[PDB]
Image (cartoon, rainbow over all chains, first blue to last red; front, side, top):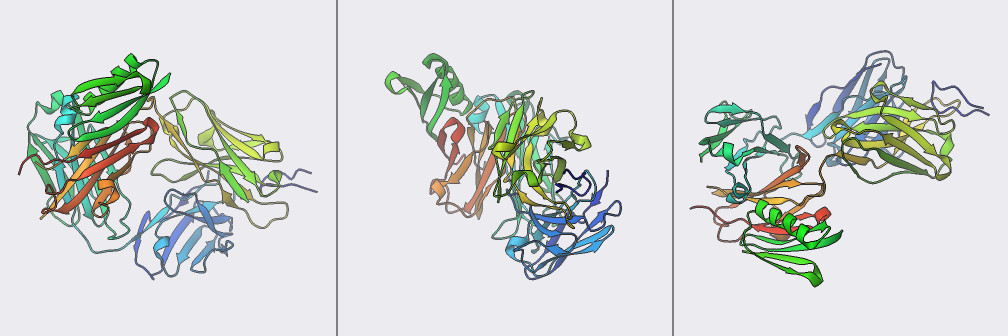
Length: 13
Length: 211
Length: 57
Length: 218
């Protein structure tokens, strides 16, 4: 799964 | 990057009335837009997100509208608690700019300031200082300008101003203005004057004394 | 440093204030400047057991 | 769920501050943390943000250089550091949680810290001078409270039994020291027949004084 803290940040898996 | 203009800076209203605040974005912002309330001495609190959505536990009177660049915030019947500051915020691209904010104040009948002047105390003079004080009390509306004169000459340097928030009981405003000089400079001039300009009087409201 | 106290007994100014200082003689200078800045001029005592100065008009 | 910030800070020009923001009630690394500045009578300014999962910080253009965000993940805490402080840093600082996640439709700041005050001054603790304000159908009196540091001072009239007719003004920092004033208004048959006294407290110097306002002519 992905963590995405803002709309324009890249997701971290 | 992207500018958020919030008009007007100050808004007058009464209990049970409705008010509308605008917010214009510099670019298209979609609906990535939030509204916050800030009471005096407290932190901001979210009221509306996604332009139109009410945050949880927030009362029905609050609402928001718009998308693109034009946005509004409405309160439908005002209570005592509502007369504080409100900010819009753009959340589309960094930096996430806030609007300049609007303060809601309570409307009342116009009232002239009560103006009082005080020379330096002998206590202060002994220490080598000299502060001349004016109180300009219980006026409405809030806009007012104070000018100091020494022997008829306008003086800006050494002046320290402070202002209260709207009174909870009578809805007026007050102001304090202190002109501080050295004892030595104070003893070289004779006439001291503070002059208040306010909507209630065509001429300045002045108090004065000769040393 | 140690906390010294000043009890003020003026004609119109009354109460107390404190200062943190290396010794009593240094605290005394701070206190006499304090009284002067407040228009208080009078007689001084000092009690070493309680670290307390007094100025009275 | 809470954001709990550290307490008030007093700094001399050129020193460093570090202030904390402790989050509780949720997984700390799920959401990022945003920092705002509010100068005394001014509006909210977004300084930047830190990714709580990644450690990557982003600074707004006005906050590049002296400003540094950091994390202590095991204590669920974010920090704001300001190096080489100056007069322009005197303000209140807030942290706020950015609510967003993968697949979310919405973005907003839901939880905010209670805010923390920074004051920049060369001054050390200094007790106030209290000066009387007397004139020379109603009468207005006052006390002028000059030359103290730091905030706050507290002021009442006749030990709190005169509360109507009172205006106590917010303190202003002028050149490293504070000044505050207060007026009280009574009927002219009241004073000087009955005494009127202002009670001034400045907890930081443990000062508690009473100043009687005596008349200075008819």
